[PDB]
DNA sequence: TTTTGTTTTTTTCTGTCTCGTGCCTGGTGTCTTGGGTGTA
DNA sequence: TACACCCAAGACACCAGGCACGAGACAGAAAAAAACAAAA
């Protein structure tokens, strides 16, 4: 992790890939790549959640912040389409035909 | 016995208001309860199968997570 | 003086906004737990359940019901109607692939 | 678990923002799901090419197939940078 | 001379195309569109006949399913003719 | 090349699905959706074509790209 | 195969399970069970297809026969719900609203 | 290139001695067999990984069949698998 | 009351179906030893 | 968690029908006339 400049563990990812019964041999660049991708995804999600929390005057990330960060982003909603977030709720979307005319 | 009536009318009304439903009819609650019972049975069958495959008598959260993932309802926040 | 009375449509949208702003569990805990235990008893007798498993089941059921209600409202609005009908739920469950 | 790593990533992207236990569990579940998906895609890609070794190319292909568009491009760039920094 | 009513030929074509399983999309325009779309992703690409046939079959099946959902949505709205709003609602419910 | 799918072709495709009457703004619209479908499949297959160090999109790549999205296709294995 | 009374190969299934990157070790009854399940499914599908072909006056099985045999059965259609059959078509189902009178 | 065309033809002759099969139908049956094989193998591998088990036996395949196949199909497949295991062990 | 979809009855070639048949590849006995369950 | 136990993985040696290459033929789509109930 220190040689690749990543916060996610490289040895743990390598051990998980070796014990997960995915392939006979595992290279040295695949765990680094997977850890980097996971770290980038986590960083994007956490930044969006922190922005949503700052928009609500909150200092702690709650599942509602994660839901608002995932649903507002198009790519994050496409990647997590069939993903359900517990205690996250939904978006405050009201149809125009239901408003008082 | 007859626990399907636990999901009373106000619960279904709140669940509809969360989804953006303005007006609710009368025959909506029965169909909602039936669909909820069908979904609960479909999930609990796989949960009990996963629990019996582990030779256990207590349905843990991991079994429910696996049963929901094998169906198509990926749920987070219950893997710890 | 006649007491205050809201016209049909105001408190409905108010409750919509209130339940869309908050993410609390709308289904009660004890009836849902009893229903889950009764359903699990039909498959295997003498079954224990943890709090985390029941909470995850309740969250998944609430999310699925919210999605189904969204689809039902969409189908009802598509048919030039405001009140939801079981035909909309049937159409939503048929298009989604459940039936 | 991935608690300390997620906390460090959050401190890197937000020095003045905390995280609850439920949010930490949700992040850990998301990380585990992405890990499983990418590992399965890499195993499938290795089995389709009669290969018994998963390298960085398989992970890059899995990321390009799973992640959509700009997310996939940025993840591929980050993975390539990490691989070039680790190999050097 | 004879003249069919607006509804008989439609049902006849429905029955004829539901009894037969032949490809309803031409080969050359579909192949040209597939090549033009694949050119935007990677240049200098070749395609096999089996791959083009599989793509055509998958596209035809997806279009048939989408048209079934569209007809269902149109009938649910007390209508016979299909509208783009029906296709939009079907694609929104399906999650596309 | 989106104009290759003629309107009577979409009419036949709708007749296969049980559609009695078709409007005028359907075909073109459906055409776009069709493009989206290809834009959600071919590219993925192209990715497979970029994984085997090949330049020809085989049927196996198309089958894998269709299975990876839930649209399992038979008769091309 | 001959000892278990099944026409499907057991050694081939065992080799595919060993080299399929599923587990470190494969038991002796797992390939037999999987071959038996595959044989039962294939027998049911082929019997339904032969019945559909006899109903169509043909001594061969075509993709249309397989589609008419799978889509007609409820459990077989539920198992292959997200499965597209090439050159199989759809069921000749017309809604009652589109019918005259 | 290996395929289960011979075994599919044998099963067809067993269930229908006077009925053939086309090439496209044979390919569709091969794809169906491959898909069922892959699904059951993945489910068994997941069940073995969830229990920290590195061995896949008949119990894992039975659980995968009960989880994938619905109702009567699952029951008949489980019965056939148990009968085949009993015949092979004896 | 008259025109048009739907169903029955001749051959005739027509894409296909099982028989005839050679090479070999995967279809069977036999020694060793041992590690994954059986039962406790 | 422990003691026991027995058929498979591996390997040697021996052996038999699939599968594609042709062929005579086999039930059937078509070509075409002729005929009854229901629809317009």
Image: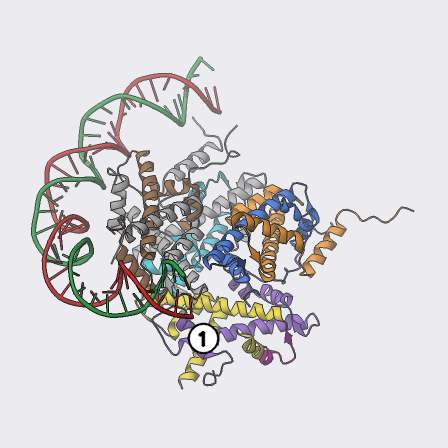
Chain colours: A purple, B blue, C orange, D yellow, F cyan, G brown, I green, J red
Is residue A94 at least partly visible in the picture?
no
- Tell me where the magenta segment starts and ends, as one range: D10-20
Q: Tell which of A90 and G99 is nearer to you.
A: A90
Residue drawn at x 42%, y 75% is A15
Q: As drawn, is I39 to the left or to the right of A6?
A: left
Q: Quadrant of residue G12?
A: bottom left
Q: Which residue is mark 1?
A: A13
Residue at coordinates 69% horizontally, 70% vertically from top-left?
Answer: A56
SS of the residue under disc 1 = helix
Q: Is residue D79 magenta?
A: no
Q: Residue I35: x percent and y percent?
A: 32, 68
Query: Does the image show residue D53?
Result: yes
Residue C46 point in image, percent of width and height? 55, 52
Q: Pick whichever, B52 or G81, lies toward us.
A: B52
Q: Is residue B38 above or below residue A37?
A: above
Q: Residue at x 55, y 54 (%)?
A: C47
Q: In this image, D48 relative to C66: left or right?
A: left
The chain holding disc 1 is A
**Which residue appears farthest toward the right when viewing the image?**
C1
In the rendered view, tell whether residue F7 sits above or below residue J28. Answer: below
Q: Position of residue C36 (x, y in %)?
A: 59, 52
Percent of width and height locating residue B78: 56, 64
> Is D15 one of the magenta-colored residues?
yes
Q: Is residue A98 above or below residue G95?
A: below
Residue C55 figure quarter: bottom right
């Amino acid at each position: 992790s220190s040689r690749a400049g990543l916060q996610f563990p490289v040895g743990r990812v390598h051990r998980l890939l070796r014990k997960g019964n995915y392939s006979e041999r595992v290279g040295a660049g695949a765990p680094v790549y997977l850890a980097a991708v996971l770290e980038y995804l986590t960083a994007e999600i956490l930044e969006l959640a922190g922005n949503a929390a700052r928009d609500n005057k909150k200092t702690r990330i709650i599942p509602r912040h994660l839901q608002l960060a995932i649903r507002n982003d198009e790519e994050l909603n496409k990647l997590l389409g069939r993903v359900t977030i517990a205690q996250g709720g939904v978006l405050p979307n009201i149809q125009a035909v239901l408003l008082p005319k | 016995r007859d626990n399907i009536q636990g999901i009373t009318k106000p619960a279904i009304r709140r669940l509809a208001r969360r989804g953006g439903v303005k007006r609710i009819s009368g025959l909506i609650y029965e169909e909602t309860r039936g669909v909820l019972k069908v979904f609960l049975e479909n999930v609990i069958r796989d949960a009990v199968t996963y629990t019996e495959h582990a030779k256990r008598k207590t349905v843990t959260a991991m079994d429910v997570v696996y049963a929901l993932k094998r169906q198509g309802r990926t749920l987070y926040g219950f893997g710890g | 003086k006649k007491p205050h009375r809201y016209r049909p449509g105001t408190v409905a949208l108010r409750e919509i906004r209130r339940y869309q702003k908050s993410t609390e569990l709308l289904i009660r805990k004890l009836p849902f737990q009893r229903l889950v235990r009764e359903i699990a008893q039909d498959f295997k007798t003498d079954l224990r359940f943890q709090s985390a498993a029941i909470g995850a089941l309740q969250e998944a059921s609430e999310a699925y019901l919210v999605g189904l209600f969204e689809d039902t409202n969409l189908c009802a609005i598509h048919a030039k109607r405001v009140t939801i009908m079981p035909k909309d739920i049937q159409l939503a469950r048929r298009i989604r692939g459940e039936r | 678990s991935y608690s300390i790593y997620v906390y460090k990533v959050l401190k890197q992207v937000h020095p003045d923002t905390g995280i609850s236990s439920k949010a930490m569990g949700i992040m850990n579940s998301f990380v585990n799901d992405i890990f499983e998906r990418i590992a399965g895609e890499a195993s499938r890609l290795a089995h389709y090419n009669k290969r018994s070794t998963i390298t960085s190319r398989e992970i890059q292909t899995a990321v390009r197939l799973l992640l959509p568009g700009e997310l996939a491009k940025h993840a591929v760039s980050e993975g390539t940078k990490a691989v070039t920094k680790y190999t050097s």
